Image (cartoon, rainbow, N blue to C red):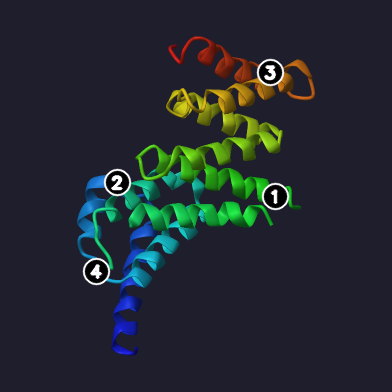
Amino acid sequence: SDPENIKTQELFRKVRSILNKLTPQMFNQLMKQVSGLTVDTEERLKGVIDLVFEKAIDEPSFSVAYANMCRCLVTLKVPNFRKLLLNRCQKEFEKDKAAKDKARRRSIGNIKFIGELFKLKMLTEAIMHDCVVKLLKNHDEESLECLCRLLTTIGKDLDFEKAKPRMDQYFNQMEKIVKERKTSSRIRFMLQDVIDLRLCNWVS
């Protein structure tokens, strides 16, 4: 395409610039920055979105920022945003199903980001369940703490009358992890907190 290839180039560079400020940008400045972008193509929206995930995978810690970034991009029409997001998210999942004990570390980062996106309504409760199942699968301290923090924050939202059964199972799997002391008493107290919470109808 040649001349278009040039604008797609500048777009991507502008987006890498936005993401590459060593000091995470807050929402307001994000809206002004994103308004200086031209995402007029699906290949472009998908590329920008890819750029964001790649950054969020490198610095999971700033996933609140990147999620806010995404929150700004969803204010654009292109010849369907959440769809590309979901698709992009399930990519890590559909790929995680394929030191594969270091994949857990990367998995924790991704889930933190995905959870940040879910908190801004850009993702489905269905993908959160995938996350929970993935966290229970790996029963290491990091995964469990991620699980405890996640469920503490979004637990009741996921706890819908129709999801009650799967949630019932998650929590019974956690109690089992407690009962068997192959985990630190610390993680065991954290686990018992999420269980206490739920038993208390998610009221503190």
- State the separation of the CA atoms marked 2 and 1: 31 Å
Mark toward the start of the polypeptide (4 vs 3): 4
Mark toward the start of the polypeptide (2 vs 4): 2
User: Crowding near pointer 1: few (<14 within 10 Å), some, many (20+)?
Assistant: few
- Amino acid type, residue under disc 3 in the picture: Glu
Mark toward the start of the polypeptide (1 vs 3): 1
Q: Quadrant of the N terminus?
A: bottom left
Residue at the disc numbered 1: 102
Which label is found at residue 26?
2
Q: Quadrant of the C terminus?
A: top left
- State the separation of the CA atoms marked 2 and 4: 20 Å
Q: Are marks 3 and 2 in contact (CB under 8 Å)?
A: no
Residue appearing at x 49%, y 60% in the figure = 54
The residue closer to the viewer here, 161 or 96, is 161
* Residue 100 in the image: above or below residue 127: below
Residue at the disc numbered 3: 175
- State the separation of the CA atoms marked 4 and 3: 50 Å
Residue appearing at x 24%, y 54% in the figure = 75
* Residue 166 in the image: above or below residue 99: above
The residue closer to the viewer here, 26 or 78, is 78
- Amino acid type, residue under disc 4 in the picture: Thr
Residue appearing at x 56%, y 40% in the figure = 131
- State the separation of the CA atoms marked 1 and 4: 37 Å
Residue at the disc numbered 4: 38
- Amino acid type, residue under disc 1 in the picture: Lys
